[PDB]
Picture 1 (tube, rainbow, N blue to C red):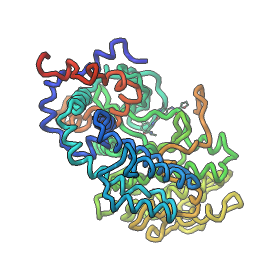
Picture 2: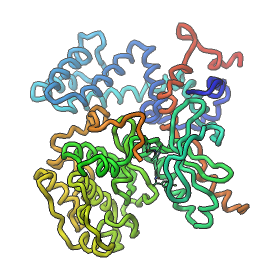
Picture 3: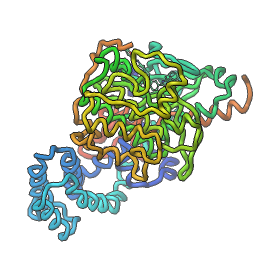
Picture 4: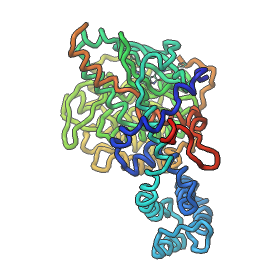
Length: 503
Ligand SMILES: Cc1[nH]c(/C=C2\C(=O)N=C3CC=C(C(=O)N[C@H](C)c4ccc(F)cc4)C=C32)c(C)c1NC(=O)c1ccco1
């Protein structure tokens, strides 16, 4: 449901308007041709016009397909890629991989199919495209078209950019609504934070820290920030909409209470990936409880409520007795210097609670004081039942290690150590990261699973930074605004908006 004149709102500016962008955007290959979705598509499209570059894009696609193929179907897919791209007789043969590398992948196959068989090749292909082909693209009409898309991306964002609907959720500093971009029709979840409630409460550094954390991370398993704008009365955060309910509701109201181990395996895998993406920015979550794990329309989960998250300086630790009773690691309850370890304790709490249907230190039918819940977390060893496989008991016992030094995933290796745990032995993380594994529960679409100071003006400028690059470009592609607007001249000629002669 796009606006009536959405083609006028996203109307491409004349290429002459982007000269300032041309001389400020860093010409980074990985950023302009891979990370940024629209730049990626435009660079691919530029390679579509060259017969030599074409075969290199098709191969990377075929390797991406190879990485997610089942194990019993690797050798089949591997031989296909070989006899189509890496055969010197082929029509779409890759010539920029040395003859002493095509030979190696032929041996690798003879040995045994490995899911990274073409990793060496793919890297050589990128080693070639980052050179000449990339610098030719920079002087092509497709990079000028990219500058036009960046220009639109940079445009200011106000309340009139969105269409507010219904108040779906509440909390602290404000409420959570559901908004829609008028020009594209994509649904989001506004997080209206009332300004008066932030000044009176002197928590401006907490709201800015949450926005910066939300924008810096992009993950399929954490709520993403798309826009940050100020409105006269509140400071809004536009986040991923999640309409499938939260994990607490599904554990207890839809559960046994609890899930089958296999079903909990799926959610734990996605949660673990969410934590790994957060930890890549050395950011600790500290708020892992079932009601913060939300489900989307398809049944996948994202981590939500990053208001308790903080960015840990590399090589440093932090203090903070924060979180929810029952979901605080011992090092947090003791108010010690900790790192990312609280999140792996939380992950243990979640896996246990999903399988067993209750918290590892508080029975569902038990009524105990906050103090006794902490004593158990610090002294009592949790007990397991026949709902847990030996592998499930293991990973939970290791993640619930009282000593953060011996806790799983809390070594220099990080989330990788948790992904090898026998509990995930039947989990293909590559296919999960690529969205190829069907969720165990698909929500029904029609479901309802539920003052004039200047220092304030300086705090609003650092917050209301506008649209977020990657989410915005993804919004354009998903809504098919990119497909419809990204048109050129007939027979590969310059369109008017890209011709500097007549503006
Ligand atoms: C559209 C919609 N959006 C949300 C909330 C979210 C969403 O999507 N994505 C995030 C990210 C992050 C948060 C978050 O910070 N939460 C904490 C506590 C918080 C903090 C401060 C506040 F002022 C308020 C809340 C919330 C959300 C919900 C729950 C729904 N509707 C349903 O799920 C639903 C449909 C039918 C039956 O139920």
